[PDB]
Length: 310
Image (cartoon, helix red, strand yellow):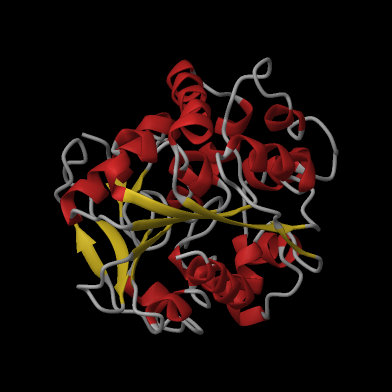
């Protein structure tokens, strides 16, 4: 229905620090003909599941230093690549990627594998979609590890989650420029600029899925979805506040990447207040937007808090 393409498998031969075996589902409901990739790691029978959600413009490769810490703890880690990202398939047209289209895919993935005992792990778009999951089926979520993210709300009801779109000009205005404007978007240069600590090898891992620009339509639509929020996304995200503030009784863990210009403190302190029971965040001073690149430290501490309150 949705014309889509798939990335040559050879694009991933040389990945650094990605020894994970691939799994695929290609029959989600609503998602015909489309194949999705996801990591399934650790004891595939563990009580606890860490569902790890990626954001713009990355993939599961992102969680790569986190995954094993979670597996070695005795958890099963799921870690899906969205349609248009990593190893999943990619619709060719930006008109096909919407907020529901990626959200429904999430709910579909969750039903299908039947996950329970979830410790939701979000950042970026992964949190924007991922934080609307719980109210869908509350009985299946038990914890949350939230890194630099928030809810796509409409200006009035939460100004902090709209404000960063316009100011600073070297924050979200700059991120969106680097993404939707180049005719020749090199995600290795982009990442090396938004994450100065990456090595040339890592950076190249984030361009692997995209050989040419026709593979990038979903890379392209995401910043624009931050900018232009449709009604469903507003209603849904508005409905999520209420759930995190009044319904949620789960355990949480927050880590802030203080060097972030898009979603640092301005956005994280206000989120910390709407999550019923969210404790004193963990401020990572040398980290940017991609907190997961100071990942092990997060994964470790997140599990250390997790047990000290069980």
